[PDB]
Image (tube, rainbow, N blue to C red):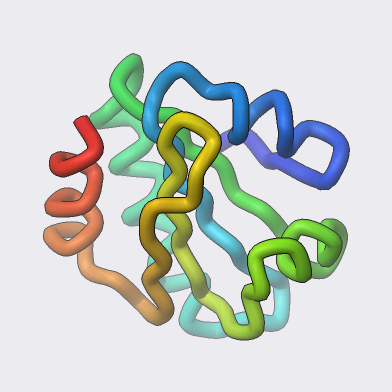
Length: 104
């Protein structure tokens, strides 16, 4: 999964032509490791249909501040430049797929 930061956010996320799923994580976050596999898998499965990125809050806090993200793991969904939904915690693959499906 491609990393996204403060400098590529507008381009990669806000100007995307397809729905975007963003995974907010950090090296010290334990539960984050549990969803990492699920994120990579979904990115592959929906290639060409959605864009997936991961944002390390340690290196791009500016974005976390913009959307008022205060806890991780957090998964955000964007579509046409707008934040459509926020999910906190170790989300199961099935729940993420339900969301991906509604934005398609």
